[PDB]
Image: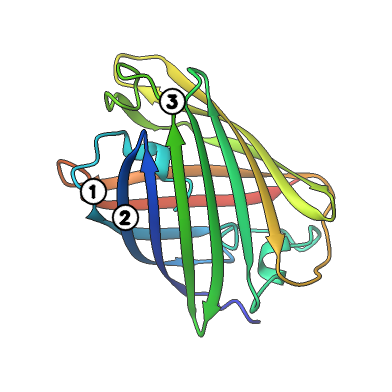
Amino acid sequence: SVIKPEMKIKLRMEGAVNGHKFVIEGEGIGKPYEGTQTLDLTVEEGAPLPFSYDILTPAFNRAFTKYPEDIPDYFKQAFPEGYSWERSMTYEDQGICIATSDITMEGDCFFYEIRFDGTNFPPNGPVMQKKTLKWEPSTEKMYVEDGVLKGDVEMALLLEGGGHYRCDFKTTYKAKKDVRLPDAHEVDHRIEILSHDKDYNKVRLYEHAEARY
């Protein structure tokens, strides 16, 4: 098929959180049909990041999802032409992020151009005080609306002092060509920062994702 069993990834994210501009370069590799991938990410502008890196990690490609044969795979169908997504992330303390990504393919390599913007995070909140530990595993509900695919997922960041910091993700996924559309289903996620240097200038990031009814 067009999507090979092993695919490389190159990316750039440009963004700003509470007005702090940053840029991150990324390269990685994954297995699209097994729904796994690992990225090496490097801050190239705006170091040291004054906010929690975890708010960024889900912005760093549902092509990397294990899809059963009887659910149409919106994402792998979309290539070689590719697809884009747009996402709002509404945190429980009125911090808000918006991200977009345009995903293309050249050979055995995905390319992402990501924009990430976040505003209104409280100065003593867990994002600006870097109190987050990891995202809890999640279940994203995939559904069709306006001829495209949407995903809604209730997210929670585990916090240092125990407790959780919650966020509602809404994503719209837009294939660049006509594809077969699935029925409502779910995608189970696990995302982990495997390793990082002190200020998260270097980060190694892993996701596993699998679709089902």
Where does residue 150 sit, x and y in percent of width and height?
72, 47
- Residue at label 2? 23
At label 3, counting other C-alpha atoms closer than 10 Å, the crowd grade (few under 14, some 14-19, many 20 or more) is few
- The residue depicted at 52 percent of the width and 19 percent of the height is 92
Mark 2 and 1 residues: CB-CB less than 8 Å, in contact? yes
Residue situated furthest left in the rendering: 198
Q: Please, what is the three-letter code of the amino acid marked with disc 1?
A: Gly
Q: Residue drawn at (19%, 47%), measured in percent from left and top? A: 47
Please tell me whether residue 208 is drawn above or below residue 188 in the rendered image.
below
In this rendered view, identify the residue nearer to me: 100 or 149.
100
Residue on which disc 3 sits: 120
Pick whichever of labels 3 and 1 is earlier in the sequence: 1
Left or right: 101 as drawn, with respect to 53: right
Quarter-of-image position of residue 23: bottom left
Front residue of 116 and 187: 116
Q: From the viewer's perspective, is residue 198 above or below residue 181?
A: above
Where residue 46 is drawn, which disc sits there? 1
Instruction: Classify residue 164 as left or right of residue 82.
Output: left
Alpha-carbon span between mark 2 and mark 1? 7 Å
Which residue sits at x=38%, y=62%?
12
If you read the primary sequence from the N terminus, does the residue marked by circle 2 or circle 1 appear first?
A: 2
Going from N to C along the chain, the mark reached first, 3 or 2, is 2
Query: What amino acid type should be assigned to the residue bearing mark 3?
Result: Asn
Give whichever of 201, 208 is nearer the camera: 201
> Which amino acid type corresponds to the residue marked 2 in the rendered image?
Val
